[PDB]
Image: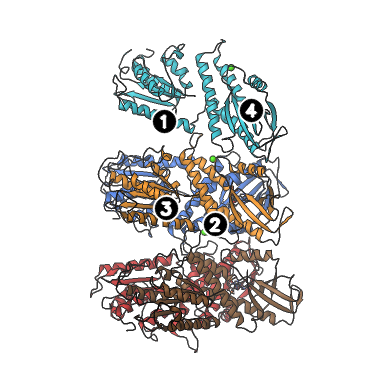
Chain colours: A blue, B orange, C red, D brown, E cyan
Amino acid sequence: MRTRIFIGSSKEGLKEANYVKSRLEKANFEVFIWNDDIFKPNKNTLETLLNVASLFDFGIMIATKDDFDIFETVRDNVVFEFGLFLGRLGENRAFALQENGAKLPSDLLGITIPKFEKTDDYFSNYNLNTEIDNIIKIINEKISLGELGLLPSTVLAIGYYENFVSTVCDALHSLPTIKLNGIEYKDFVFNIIIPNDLDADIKRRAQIYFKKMDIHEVKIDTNGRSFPLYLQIDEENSGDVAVLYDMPTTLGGIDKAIEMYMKKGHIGKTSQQQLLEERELRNFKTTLINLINNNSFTKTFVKVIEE
Amino acid sequence: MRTRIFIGSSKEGLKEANYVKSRLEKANFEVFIWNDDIFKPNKNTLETLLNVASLFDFGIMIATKDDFTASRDDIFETVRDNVVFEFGLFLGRLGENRAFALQENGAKLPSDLLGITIPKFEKTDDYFSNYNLNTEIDNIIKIINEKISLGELGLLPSTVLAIGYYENFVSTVCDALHSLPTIKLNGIEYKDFVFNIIIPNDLDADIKRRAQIYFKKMDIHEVKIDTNGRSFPLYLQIDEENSGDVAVLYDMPTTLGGIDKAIEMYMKKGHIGKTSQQQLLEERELRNFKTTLINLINNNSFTKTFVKVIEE
Amino acid sequence: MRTRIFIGSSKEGLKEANYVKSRLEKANFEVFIWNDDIFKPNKNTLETLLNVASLFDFGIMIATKDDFDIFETVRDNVVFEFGLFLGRLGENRAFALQENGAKLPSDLLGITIPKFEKTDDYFSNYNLNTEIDNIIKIINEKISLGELGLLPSTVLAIGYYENFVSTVCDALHSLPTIKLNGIEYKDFVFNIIIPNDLDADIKRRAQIYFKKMDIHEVKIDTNGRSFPLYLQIDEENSGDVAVLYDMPTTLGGIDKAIEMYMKKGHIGKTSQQQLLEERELRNFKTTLINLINNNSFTKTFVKVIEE
Amino acid sequence: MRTRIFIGSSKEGLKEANYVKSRLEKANFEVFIWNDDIFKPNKNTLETLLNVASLFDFGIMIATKDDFTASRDDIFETVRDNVVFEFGLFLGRLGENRAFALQENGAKLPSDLLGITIPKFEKTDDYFSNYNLNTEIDNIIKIINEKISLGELGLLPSTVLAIGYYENFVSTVCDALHSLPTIKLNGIEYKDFVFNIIIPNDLDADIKRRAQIYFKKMDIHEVKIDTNGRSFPLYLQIDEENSGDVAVLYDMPTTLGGIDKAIEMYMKKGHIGKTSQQQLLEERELRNFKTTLINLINNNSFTKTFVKVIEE
Amino acid sequence: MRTRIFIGSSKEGLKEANYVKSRLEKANFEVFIWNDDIFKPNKNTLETLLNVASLFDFGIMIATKDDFTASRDIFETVRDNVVFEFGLFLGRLGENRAFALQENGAKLPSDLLGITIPKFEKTDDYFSNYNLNTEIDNIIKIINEKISLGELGLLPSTVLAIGYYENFVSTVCDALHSLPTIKLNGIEYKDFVFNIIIPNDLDADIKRRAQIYFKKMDIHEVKIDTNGRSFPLYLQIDEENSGDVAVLYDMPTTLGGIDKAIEMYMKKGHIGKTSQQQLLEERELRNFKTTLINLINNNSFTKTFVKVIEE
Ligand SMILES: Nc1nc2c(ncn2[C@@H]2O[C@@H]3COP(=O)(O)O[C@H]4[C@@H](O)[C@H](n5cnc6c(=O)[nH]c(N)nc65)O[C@@H]4COP(=O)(O)O[C@H]3[C@H]2O)c(=O)[nH]1
Ligand SMILES: Nc1nc2c(ncn2[C@@H]2O[C@@H]3COP(=O)(O)O[C@H]4[C@@H](O)[C@H](n5cnc6c(=O)[nH]c(N)nc65)O[C@@H]4COP(=O)(O)O[C@H]3[C@H]2O)c(=O)[nH]1
Ligand SMILES: [Ca+2]
Ligand SMILES: [Ca+2]
Ligand SMILES: [Ca+2]
């Protein structure tokens, strides 16, 4: 799916925030402003950058000279929200764009804060346009290399990859001929089923998906592990290439953790919980795809398939 | 081990931070201050928050009425802006569940900032008689001990790894062994079982290879357990010479390999050696995994007295 | 149905109670005052605040200076009735609105009691209107999230859901083709019939409802239980989608629970027993709907239909 | 087990509360006072009522002529309104059926507060000879024992769960088996049957999974029974090994899974561990479920000597 | 040994270079200036920066406001010579091993390809300038933090050390740690130590040198079976000086490959060794030893069990 970007700004900076959102939207991006219709339960602008700021891939903060409530000074509120945004989104996923006359620094912890002139027609300013273009270019290169972070879904994907997918690929590639359930195959494909959402238990969902698709079970012996690899094979749609299937079970762990940490004494899901679940699924899928594409033995033999 | 607490302050808050650190050490804690010898690579007092402030269990912010003025700090044009930005960065790095704040009277900070109470105390030379600061530190200690005793959880990679490992392997193994009228593993009958989970000392070696050589050195033999909670049998390791009356089972978690390689991929630049931040992150991940696993084990009647977490 | 809200007040707070009731009615709420025409058998304001106050979704208390009979002091009466209110409605279903200057603590066990100026034309006080708006917003938010309590109907709904409805949906979704009684279906819908009232035995009522509507019986084999799931299918109005029916049986248990609990030395039903019956039915329906809507395998496949 | 009684009082009524508690243990009761070491998370004596006072079978208050004055309490501006509000909260948590009250001479509380008798007793240093207080405690004990002996029930979730489970499964099973001239289950003839209901010790494990592993551990075989009281046959479990002359049937109620899940969703915040209030609530739910099931079994001729409730 | 640092400057700016060399020398560093007695065969400074500049761990370049005019030696303008030697220095030493120090008024940038070029004021007594002193201190701190983490580059000795480590030393340590008891040549040991013999120089064939070292020290061969390789690990054991802790020995053979490569690259029709060849050999040996030690110290199974010992 498209990359999610959060834009934080004060009440006076909605014009700049909307212009930046539109410009990013024309660049095939998903953009949410701090007062988006998603963040209605949030009371003020401070707690939306505390609760649902890290739930986005990147973030942009806009500073306004005029903005210089909770605190006793607008300057204090601006610097506090800047610090909170930078801490929540780190130094690799955070970007800043202060207007001309704003007296914030320009090299805060490795994050540049370019200055743009305050005008009325924003389809005229070369400086603001080129700064937004630089931000877009930086975001586009990070997504293509595969910048990683200690997110739980990223670690889950890395562990799942190295301990199951690479082992399966090595075991299948180390066979002079592929003999699965007594049937010979001249090639194989490894399909990883990623659930559309974390609204159901992963184990039962995987079991019922296998039952509905009528997928049998295979056992693969590997020298890279002390116990065999257990998989699922089609046996009906697989004529010449072995069609193997698997739904990751670590997703059960992330679902249980999200349920424990989010769910208070209520049954319904808050907006923050839903955003966190979608973010975890997106990072898991993206990290798994990036890990797959960077190995010669798993590149064209493993495909990530939606449920 | 002990609970690690990070204390952030300004250049003039060293007295307050040192007193708080000493009083916390009196309460069986492991306190680190922003100016400690661990954080030497951090050039200023702001990168020590962006880097290692989130690597501690809890954090305390001390604010004094000396940085709430208009002066120069070589980073922000005003020291007040610098201290407010530092407070915001601290809160963002540690969140609303692991951040505590102490301010002296006269500071312009709020008192109900995003669910974080910031009590005021009267500054004095002798802090052993300061009732206000002493009682606020007492409340901080009480809250920290309460959140450690329940099991307050947070989406850290190690916490999620421990939860997944527990739910998918440990509970399933305990249910499989408890659903047997007699425990017959490798053709030997046992009247009881104990499931030892071996946590590595560190993450400086590959977890799979380290577990394999640990099993070889201790001479532990593999077993297979059939379960109704999974589509394929659970594979474990049994001792078979020291397990005469009670079946002794061993397992080194493999998700620790995933977290180890993730940390290697993230923190390690083009250098062989490990930075202090990487070591702190690995220690925090390992400790959090062990603590979360212990908390999950102790909150289930089927695993409370049958699974023991043992250091390598 | 509309949310039921109870207003507790003394004899001199009647104008405030009527104003709040009118505002909540304009805010799409059902409001009953302590001296409503339904609370006629109740003698004083204390026994009606003990017996039928917990039978409403939420509650509002109003304090007045003039009240500062059963006790020897009116102030003692007011604080005692406030305590009884809090004990009946807990900390999540209780709200309070004291008039200006009232000396009640403002953080009584986590419940705020805002102060409003005592005027004559109640369509003028900004403070009272914004406090009522805040109360309405809080109530509306705690209904969209599914806030849950320890009511027997809620527990019955949770158990019924997780033990029957989720199992049935998982069993039906785990089928490569839907084959019920030898008829192939391309989809299915599960209809749960909730009785209009608890004035009849649930088992016999379900049987007669089925035999009027002419619904057959089916058996479904599931891996989530030790014995097969038994349902009811239409087979006449179901052409391509399997239309299933079921009346919950625990409703009989709760029905006879109220039957034995309400000291039935007579034949007719008192007002408290009746209002409790609709409260339990409403809570059961709401909890079941919230549980259904939060599972991907039951969301669009289960429908709660009135009898 | 024993009957739990909660005693609520002020900070100066500790002597009377201790005396009454001691007499109730002399009368075979399990009494907890608001200042006990179990109610530590409750910071004051007001949160002790709103949280755990409704988790006890019965409750008793002692009121003294020390807090019916005008003083400071840091919560209410006067101690008189504080004690009256505390009385009201206690009554609201416990109602008119499970609450008892005691006042000494000089207390301004009424004596017929909504059907709750509040007798007056004389304060003295040597309380073992106070005829009024001793006879009021005796009357309270008599009333409590009368309530326990009779099937006194309230709208608790566990009580409704037990009523539904009984009247929908146990009575139907007993009627189906008693309507058979001979008991033939799985092709084996028996001259009599016994139905054992397995109540788990605690709610720390999934009830369905725990029942399944218990059945596997005891090698228990499933049976199907046809009945005219329900549209589809009843499914039960039989031993087939120890049932030589009388058929033994085992069944762990599944609605206990419902109450366990409801308690987990309600009481558990973002923490792995269990609070004291949650543990007390789970114990109370299990006790009321077992008590209601036993009372319903004993209040029917077709189930009194044929169904037995046994712990796990 | 002490870290090697090269300072390049012009003839008219040798006083700043000498002061920087002395200041680094007081900081436990080995410093050579382009006009040192080692680089006599080199004709000019340009040839020195092309041949031996990369043979040092780090490099420092000094620019002054006296060779920036439109004067007249290899190029036409002394401006061109300065910018050319700066480019050659930065290319030879890369961006992780190059440092610059221009004087006040110099025209060079301050963020040239990631290499900061601080400006200092030119005086007569350099034990007075706070700016130059703090710039040299910053350079020293950067070099110190680089040497302690283990910054690595694609040098042949670094790659040789990495391959040798991960293919022999780690495998040997895992094989020995995966033994319930250590049984080498029929003798039981309760502990082991792995000694890696690094030759003092590359002036002799590594294979024959290792063989004669083993013969002189009377070290016997052992065979170790491992699950991390398809064929066993062959080592050497003392068997006389090892009573309770087994003492194992090995001289790396990849040093033979690096010695052969250096001999093939540098010898061009003579028997004696050029100073550049000697510097390259010392650099390769030092980087091999340092990389091996760094790799050893960052593994729990090899930290206290493997020691790097001089011949
Ligand atoms: N179909 C299939 N999928 C596989 C297999 N092995 C791994 N996976 C997938 O890879 C994920 C990560 O496995 P891990 O690193 O070994 O980390 C595992 C491991 O440490 C431990 N564990 C799980 N199963 C076993 C086992 O059978 N034996 C042992 N000794 N440990 C196990 O629990 C961790 C989390 O397990 P999961 O939730 O299951 O998540 C697993 C699972 O989704 C396999 O043989 N077949
Ligand atoms: N049409 C239909 N509805 C179903 C079926 N299974 C469950 N339900 C519905 O789900 C409700 C909750 O079931 P529970 O949690 O298992 O809790 C149940 C269970 O523990 C026990 N029970 C009931 N029937 C059986 C049975 O056939 N076998 C066994 N072993 N236990 C049963 O009595 C508890 C309360 O039973 P209920 O009042 O009936 O309420 C039941 C019933 O209305 C089914 O196969 N068909
Ligand atoms: Ca979920
Ligand atoms: Ca590592
Ligand atoms: Ca040579």
- Which mark, residue E249? 4
The chain containing the residue under callout 2 comes to B
* Sequence-earlier tag: 3 or 2: 3
Secondary element at image label 1: helix
Question: Can you identify the residue that label 3 sits on?
Answer: B98
Amino acid carrying label 4: it is: Tyr
Quadrant including the C terminus of chain D: bottom right
Identified by mark 2, the residue type is Leu
Write down the quadrant of residue D216 in the picture: bottom right
Q: Mark 1 or 4, which is nearer the eye?
A: 4
Q: Quadrant of the N terminus of chain D?
A: bottom right
Do marks 4 and 2 both belong to one polypeptide chain?
no
Q: Secondary structure at mark 2?
A: helix
Q: Position of residue E168 (x, y in %)?
A: 62, 31
In the rendered structure, the residue with mark 1 lies on which chain?
A: E
- Are the residues flagged by discs 4 and 3 in contact, CB closer than 8 Å? no
In three-dimensional space, the C-alpha distance between marks 3 and 1, rounded to whole angstroms, equals 34 Å
